[PDB]
Length: 121
View (cartoon, rainbow, N blue to C red):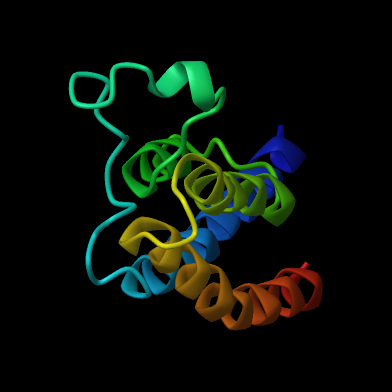
């Protein structure tokens, strides 16, 4: 159908907007603390602590499979990156601190993306 294609152009454009959002969020992590999944070789107990691991490469794979239906699903995954870190790591660690800074700085980007998603539909 013609509608399914119209829809697919929207999802494709959402994917386009979310790609740019993902790039902006990832720039707020210059130390690359959140770039890749926590290694289960190097933290073998990790899944005993954290039930839904997340990281920027894993989000990117989902994005490129147009696996995000709306901004809310994308935000959910960003929030997991931050929240998982703030649980596993103590307050006085470079890792916890990095998550706080990413949350704070990401807020601004996510604020405008919500307005852009509502505005452009």
